[PDB]
Image 1 (cartoon, rainbow over the protein chains, first blue to last red):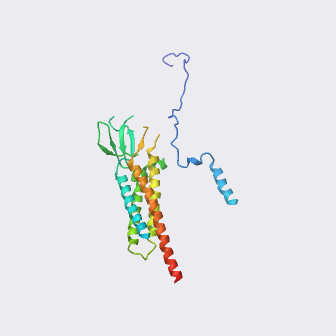
Image 2 (image 1 turned 90 degrees about the vertical axis):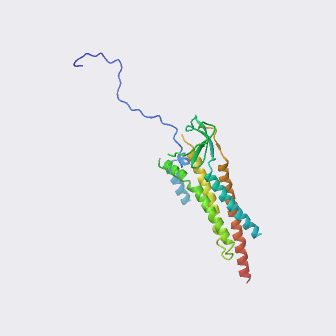
Image 3 (image 1 turned 30 degrees about the horizontal axis):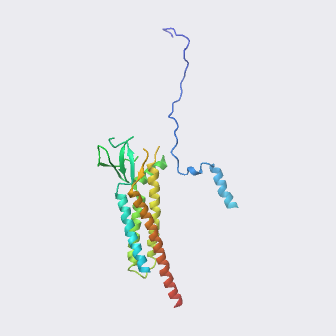
Length: 51
Length: 185
């Protein structure tokens, strides 16, 4: 701008983040526990013990 | 009788060992389509170690399989080593040897027991190897199929379990005979 003259921006932008699209993750061993949180499983174990 | 049961046990041990060695050495486990076939890809028949192209310009050439996330790494290692089918074959061999010894040291009755334990453990190891193989093949190129080597492994598993049953029955009969003879004496 010190040596030329600009116009008002015709397109405003900024820095941003590019990532690879999340894919269907390869199922993990012990993915059969995913429907319930770990805390539920531990409470189940200790309720079994207590009962 | 006892003799025929022992004969069946030894025959089954030999047959299962042979089938499993054949399946391990053989390279006809999986029929699929692969990118590295010189033209989604070309037909291939694979195994545990090497893969061979069929119906292609590079027909008949067989090349070592290029394997390669901690769990994925461990699975790849176990699949590459194929330690579980090999262990199954080794345990079958040792069980057959123990049976042959039982054909000599007729007094020691805790031998035809080790044979049965080894046969059952071999069946379990074969199950594990099959699971590992199937899991590792999958990734994330269709209409794939399994060959006669895979079913040789399955037959080996079935035979091993059967002969383990027979060996345990033999141990039962022998221990019962000895115990009844002793108590009545």
